[PDB]
Amino acid sequence: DLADRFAELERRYDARLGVYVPATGTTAAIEYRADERFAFCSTFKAPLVAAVLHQNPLTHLDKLITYTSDDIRSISPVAQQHVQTGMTIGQLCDAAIRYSDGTAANLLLADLGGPGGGTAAFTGYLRSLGDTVSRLDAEAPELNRDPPGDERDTTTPHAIALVLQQLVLGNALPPDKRALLTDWMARNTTGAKRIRAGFPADWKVIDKTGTGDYGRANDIAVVWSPTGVPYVVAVMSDRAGGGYDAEPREALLAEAATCVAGVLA
Image (tube, rainbow, N blue to C red; front, top):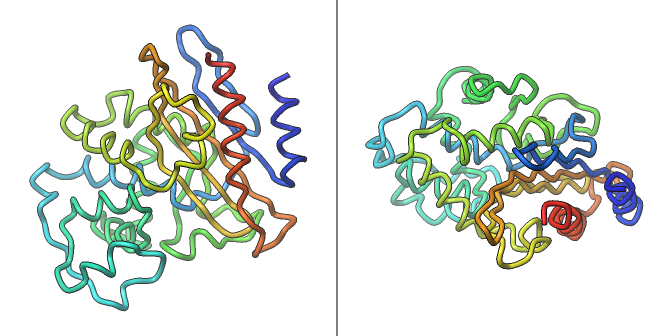
């Protein structure tokens, strides 16, 4: 019956929906179009910040990064502010997660190194976590504007949820680094209308969102029941039939999150 309700939301919203919640000791995995590819958009910024944390000393966070006004290619609510000053790797991390800053991300990719301005190193980091599916080929803003049916810059709800699970709930990062990432997602400012809206207020929610053309809207979160039981929730959608200028349906992600909550409840 769960499939039928996702299928209905699909039709109600003229959208394609993809959902995944990893299995636990007491609940089966939830999955709808869990293995079909969807555009990363900005949801990569989260495992990116963990790439940066993994490969470096804590100390590295204090390193100041200098950029110019022409480095600003995409929505950068924070970067443009500190161009005169620049930002530490820490302030870049913070903004790539909490505000989805396109430049902050573009910088951190570069701080990873190698071909494709960081993106080879980043897909390298996903590989190191067992994810053989996902791939980041381009950097902001080109990665939110791939044609529907294009492999590049995509992931699955399945693949991103297992990744996110290792980062926050698992052992991918040492505890010190673990709480940095987690704390940054808990104070994310871009997701109030998505998964977080679809879950009762007494469930704790951390997340990182993604938005793109063709009516792309994503949200990936780690939720805690009132009793403290964690689950990983990955919700992705596009609306290809509305074309490039199609509008993202936030209410789709919020509703699908409510269906998910009722089943976990």
